Length: 122
Length: 117
Length: 122
Length: 117
Image (cartoon, rainbow over all chains, first blue to last red; front, side, top):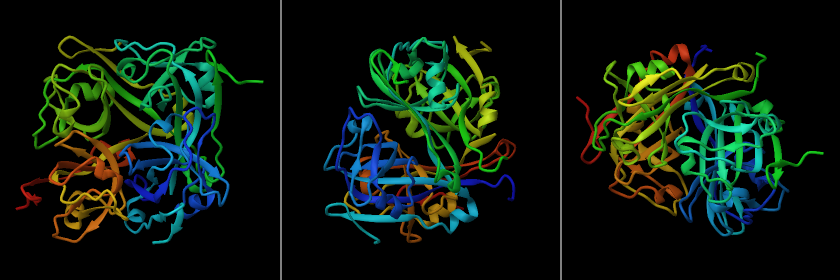
């Protein structure tokens, strides 16, 4: 309300420059991300995510499940292993929808990475 | 805030038919649609394990037990008969529900035999 | 209601196998579709549409505005002219969202084409 | 039923910066965001007239009057400085409203000069 309000698609959070740690094309299962990283970016298990590959430029859509907390895992499995490889630097983002007013004051959850998937607030 | 969540996935089915010239839609055995919660005419993503292509389309139901995965029309440029593919659909819901949501996943081997019981 | 209902993305309608009639990369303006065809497929002016190119396999997302009724126009303009050319056979679809119950009994608006963009119900 | 509608578009801007290695986001002059109704952190599509590539990302605001169109991070693989691109965002609303919706379109020439009055 107002009913019929125009709804925006906004960046909810992203993991900026994580490094892919595992990639298995033949995997019977999902992509996975350390739960600590999900938490920092506000990303949920089984939430749609975009992955934008800094190393090779590929851009694709998938979902991930939680890897154990503290594992530092970024696993890109199944068909998505044709789009990322271990060592590649990627950006992982999720988007949510909300009405325009809320969108204009929204602050995304952004976590920045370096080194061995070490996470910084800024 | 509204989240986009995996609703369900058919993991590792084989394309059985692919007709570029079809006057009609892609089709999936209704038993596989049933297992993954995927509806006739719902938006689906198809991720091709054999060639890496990733595309979006929709499917209607094929006859139960036919094991059909048919990728027709323009989509026949992105998969061929015998390719292994992963098919998923996504739904939206508020954050509060999405935190406990569980998707429907079905796994397959061989000639489209669903790992079942 | 129930509040929080799971919302599906469903095919609202499509134009099956129309032929692209104009394509201008340098165009200051939009893609356009004869209003009669929009009407048959339930597609709106300025609605997001997917175009799946049967001739060259490209798949892309755009929007169109109404061309004059009866012109039989399918015009693919701007950057999208790198994805379709005059003569190419394409499928144009739109998707809408709705709750799961409604989705299970939804019937999309499908119009089939042949010849000089002559439209049939079946 | 909920429709996805064009909210607004920047038609024919030139990319002014493209840094693959950026610790940060794509950026657009706030005056251009203002003209097309596009928000900081909103999902946008970028359609590259010069090379045909089409991708999705988001942007934050660049300084007013800077004329900046900066395509950074992985997206720097899809556009270069001097490419002409079209940037759009989409919103959703019920069918009843979408029937009369009007998007915000701004047209440009030259060095990112918005056709204005």
